[PDB]
Length: 373
Length: 190
Image (cartoon, rainbow over all chains, first blue to last red):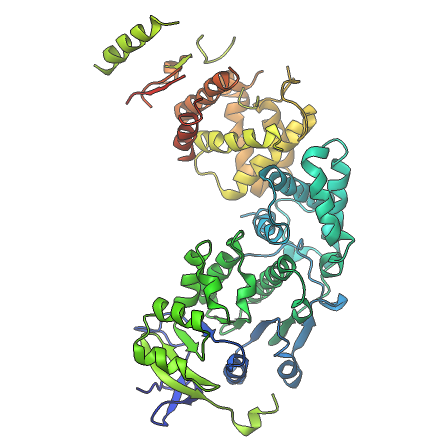
């Protein structure tokens, strides 16, 4: 049907070969936010399209922040002179316990964030254990000299406690409290000293202050699920903090392979993403969710958050879909049989573009000069 | 005539043989209390204090919990200790004192909290608790006292019939638990 805003960026071509041009910062009528949902099976063209969209928004002055488990955004980041953070290497160490603003006591809020972090990493923790874990975090902070009034802004990266201190506190308290701190301590040990210590046991090494930032969490794709999720959450909470502290307009936050964040037993992580999708409007930024495995967002435990997360954004790009994903999407977004079929037989980079209540056939393609990236 | 009906109800019930109205209003403690016993009670107290103090921020709601845990710690009881060993337990006074102690470095978090506990620690309300069932003497403070007694009266039976006359929403939730975890009967009039 054609979509052409005043100005904006070129997305691609419509069915009649005419230019689709979108201003994602528009407000008015059915343009209520600047968020995107990009969904498709692997190989469909998600990362290509997102690269185009991101490059063109960057060139118009948007800061870009990406969480990238695929290592799809490294080369772009290099071409643009942005900061590439390797989160599995020592230089990309992000300390979960370093207090940061979530989407009032900074410490109390951060402890609310840490409950989700540790529920993701340590699944199936008794309620006593959760209470005691929070007590332990409070005491470890207190020993590091940080209390309920302390402003995070002032504290140097190395003054924060780490999971090492938390582990040792729990072990010490497990002497006179073996029953409520025992298995807890043994579970923290893997992160403090064991095979996951390289992730979090040490001070934050990154000062990511740049208009193009990529958080590469690729070296985790063979890691266990709870590690994947806990680190994805930790990085997402850090990146959100970046957008909130130094708060220029039109910052685009990209969560690639967002399904990795979904956990039926800790739906709060996805709820955190949802909250991000709402609060980001307050800084005139954009949350872009990119993903396969759409059904993971629609499972009973998380659907309250997953549905809004996928469906509330003003802009959507649906490429070729997996069979289940296609049915769940067809239902969720009330696709017509024409639209459904469109998806069924869509070539790479082709599909449905949604802008508010407008939905049209689109084909995305790159200028030659955009190939370098 | 609900009081009459319930009166003869209780009278006939009496013919075969503990009720929120010993003038439990002062003289002759809401800090008296695998699964550590302390945590559960700390939950109880979330609702109790949410009843006494409205306007309570979430930061304050967490700082009060921390303070609680610490004051207990000073009393010498922690996570693994058996609450049948306590004759000795801390009281609202130690809590207030702690809060005042921490308010000098945490005025934003404990500042408007300590002054909130003054009246209950050694002021207008301290006769009720600051030391180690009828409440019509007190007719936010009444809802609070009523809830405290509800807890001390549910306990008796847990460690063993309850009339709940003229019966922070967690407060009404507590009810459903006691009224299901009966395994005496639970009478409610309103």
